[PDB]
Length: 211
Image (cartoon, rainbow, N blue to C red; front, side, top):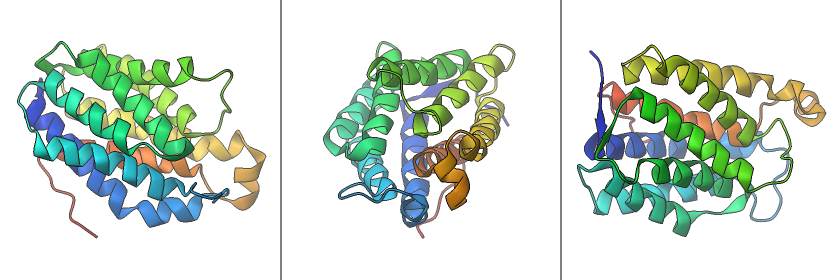
């Protein structure tokens, strides 16, 4: 089985399964956070952000991926909350901007769209802290760009993205002393990986069940 092109219907499903997988793990993500500051529970905030995106998408489906991305982007903007939820919205509003003109995308454009999200979030900060959700997103996009050059199949691509995203996540305690000593990976990066894992599920035809 393989995926050569992703249209608005499949992207909508990726968004839905990614959001549900993140929602199932939101309490986990919150509990990994070393800095549960006021209104700063990472799992809660990323879940609110992603779910607002999900809800807009579910009420305005479209087979044109660019139009669906604009709907996703709108929901992300309204839902964005917290440091990690805002970064999540920059990553995916940048992603959606990169496909706004398209009706479907191939593996190369999928990878370029992840990269466009990373560049958005980096353009919006002056020297970001390594060891955070941004680091995981950066390494995931780098992987996507490397792999897309000789993989037409978006399933195989997304699996690779997840493997390397997970490597980056597990390495975040080596970038920040506080994570190594507490003994946890970065919570925002964990939440991001939950979204990616749901994307793969959608690409495989599979449903994330509600916890």
